[PDB]
Length: 171
Ligand SMILES: CC(C)n1cnc(S(N)(=O)=O)c1
Ligand SMILES: CC(C)n1cnc(S(N)(=O)=O)c1
Image 1: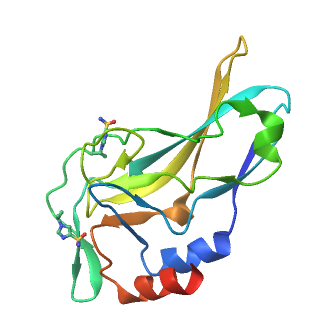
Image 2 (image 1 turned 90 degrees about the vertical axis):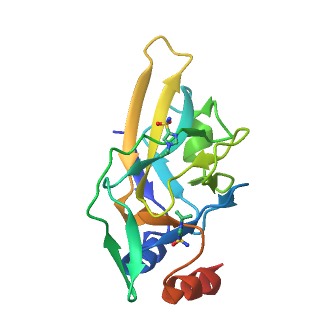
């Protein structure tokens, strides 16, 4: 069976228990922590691409009011995020299973830009999601996996200083 697991869940859970925040910039900012995924049960000889996207967890705008994150009362439909292709893609199952698949080069932006960057609505809450796409074979197949532990609010600067301190402590 195709098993997908989050590497460093212990560390993600420290961020999540504080409400995690990720910076977005016009040029794009890399994530900390980095999403690293443990994958087993691929065909070592089959061909796969690893895709990353961000699902809007709710339809609301969030604001840091008196030391606490609180959703707006005016929900709107959230357009789905664009997909980031892991740069090792396409690659053999063996490649993907020999070390954690690390999305260290994805950049989160708040502006429609050239290419590569993922465009996120600031003050929206996001749940990272991967797609494992079997390619080149006759039978195309997709397996998707969400990572609740990795939820965050896109922010142009850190609201909760406890997040700022954790980010520095573990980088
Ligand atoms: C606003 C943000 C979440 N977004 C960026 N691109 C999309 S799209 N056209 O649905 O791929 C949505
Ligand atoms: C640009 C606009 C959406 N915004 C206002 N404040 C933030 S912040 N620093 O992320 O809380 C973003």
